[PDB]
Length: 305
Length: 305
Ligand SMILES: CC(=O)/C=C/[C@H](C[C@@H]1CCNC1=O)NC(=O)[C@@H]1[C@@H]2[C@H](CN1C(=O)[C@@H](NC(=O)NC(C)(C)C)C(C)(C)C)C2(C)C
Ligand SMILES: CC(=O)/C=C/[C@H](C[C@@H]1CCNC1=O)NC(=O)[C@@H]1[C@@H]2[C@H](CN1C(=O)[C@@H](NC(=O)NC(C)(C)C)C(C)(C)C)C2(C)C
Image (cartoon, rainbow over all chains, first blue to last red; front, side, top):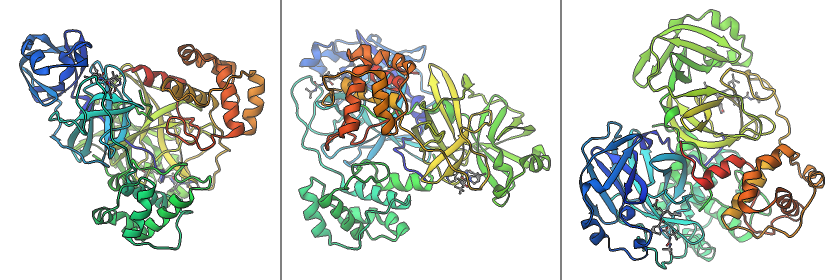
C-alpha cells in the first residue's frame, strides 16, 4: 500500500538525449534512429526570439552549423529540415539505444513523465498532467528546452511532449514531437495568455478511489446522485464536466471497490460543497487531479515495463 | 521556474534489476559486477516468515536452488552467502551495465529515489525521505521487495535502501545494502511498532527558500528570532530541533536569497503558531518536509548527472 506521485522509469529515454548547439544557443535534442529532434529556436539568438522568422534563419544555416554531441561523441549532421516548431537533424549514425517508440498527441487530462535535461544530460524525472488549458505545471530552467515527456507501455515509449517555453505563474508550454504546440501558443517572446484552467474531474474521482483502496474512507457518504446533478455542482467549482465516457473509464476502479461512480460523485459533491474540515485524503489537504484512472490502477496493481 | 517533487533518472539502476526466485517466493535483486543482492526472506515460504530461522533455511539451499533471471536470460549461481538481512548470490557473469556505485547508509532527513520493481522489471520511480523514525512513506505491493533506493552524484550511484516490509498506515521499512535495517525493525511477520515520527525542520526551511526563489513570498515577516527561541516553538509542534549544522547547510540558499536562516525561522514560527489561513505555498496547503537543502539547490540550479 501507499500512494505516491510516480514517474515512469526513464532509462529508455535517457539513452536518447543529446546536446544540440547552433551558434551560441544550446539545448537538448532527442536522438532516435538517425534523426535528432529539437526545438527550432536553437537557431535563434536571444534577440531573434523576440520576433523570429525561423524559415529565414534556417536557410542561412548549413548542416555543419549544428553541433550535436551524444555524451563526449560528436554526431555528424548530414541533413536538416523544419517540421512546424521542431527541427529534424539527420545524423550519419543511428542511435543504438533507440527504444521501440511512437509519437502521440495526448489529450488534456492525460499524464506523462518529464525527463528534465540540461546540456543533453538528464537531471530529474517527474510526473505531469496536460492541463485543460494545454499547459503543464513543470519545473524547467534556462537550457531545459528539448526535454521530452513520455509514457511507457510494456516496451514502447510514447513520446508526447517537447519543452519550449514558460508562462506566468511557472506554467509551461511545448509541442508534440511533430512540432505542433499544445494550446494557442507560438514560439516567440511576446505577450501571450493561457486560457483559464479547470480541475480534471475524472482524475479527482480516480484519486478518491485510490484513497479507498488505501483505506482512507472517511469521505464516503450514504448518498447517490445523477450525472446531471453532479455536473451542475461541479461547474460552480470550476470542475470539468464528467461524461459517460469518463464513467466507463472509471469502471475498473468502481468494480474493484464496489463503489458505483455516481456514488463516488455524491461523495465528491459533498467535499466540494462543505470542504474537508481540516482533514486530509492520502496525506493531501487539497483534492488531487493529476492521477488518471490508469495511473491509479497501474500503481495499485504493479504494472511493469 | 516551477517546483516539483523530482526523482533521479533511473536508467543506471534499471540496468541492474533482476528477478530472484527460490522455491515459490519471487522478488527483486540488484546485480552489480558478479553479485546479486536481495532480501534474505526469498528463502522463506509465507509460513516461515511468521517466525523464520534464516541461517537454518539457508543451509538447506544450494546454489542451483536460486533462479536468477536478467530479462529473459538465466544467470547461473556459483556461490551464496548471507550478510545481515540480505543475500549475496555470486553469479558466473558480471553485469556489463554496472554503474560506478557505492553503498551508503543515509541519515534521517535525507532523501533518495526509489525504483519500484516487480518480477525484476521497473514499474515507476519516486522520491522518498528517510523519516526521523527510520521509515519511509513509499508505494509498495506484494512482490516489490528488493526494490532499491538511491542517489546519483555525477556518474556515481549511491545505493542506500533495499525494501523489505510494510508497517501500519502504509509506511515502509528496509535495510541498507549491507543488510542492516534502518530503525528498530526485524524481518519477521510479528508485531513491531515504529517510533513517533517528527517533522524535518531543516527541510521545511529549505522548501520555504524554494518558495521565495519561485516568487511565493507572502509568508515572509519582518522579524528575526534566536535559534533557542525557535526551537522552543518547534518542539511544541513536533518539529526536530534545528542545529547550527543545519544552519550552515542552509547557507547557500540563505546567501542566494539574502534571507538569513534565523529570519526564515521567524517566518516559519509564525506559520506554525497561526497556520496558513487557507493560503498555499508552492501549491501546497501543508508545509512540506521531504526536500533537502541540496534537493532545492539542485532543482533550482539544474544539476545534471
Ligand atoms: C535554449 C533553451 O534551452 C530554451 C528553453 C526555455 C525554457 C524556459 C526558460 C525559463 N523556464 C522555461 O521553461 N525557453 C525559452 O526561453 C523560451 C524561448 C523564447 C522565450 N522563452 C520563454 O520561455 C519566455 N517566456 C515568454 O516569453 N512567455 C510569454 C510568451 C510572454 C508568455 C521567458 C520565460 C524566457 C520569458 C522562446 C519562446 C522562443
Ligand atoms: C516477496 C516480496 O516481494 C516481499 C515484499 C513485501 C513488501 C510488502 C508487501 C505489502 N507491501 C509491502 O511493502 N514484504 C513482506 O511481505 C514482508 C515479509 C514478511 C511480512 N512482510 C510484511 O511486509 C508484513 N508486514 C508486517 O508484518 N508488519 C509488522 C511487522 C506487523 C509491522 C505484511 C505487510 C505482509 C503484513 C516479512 C517481514 C519477512
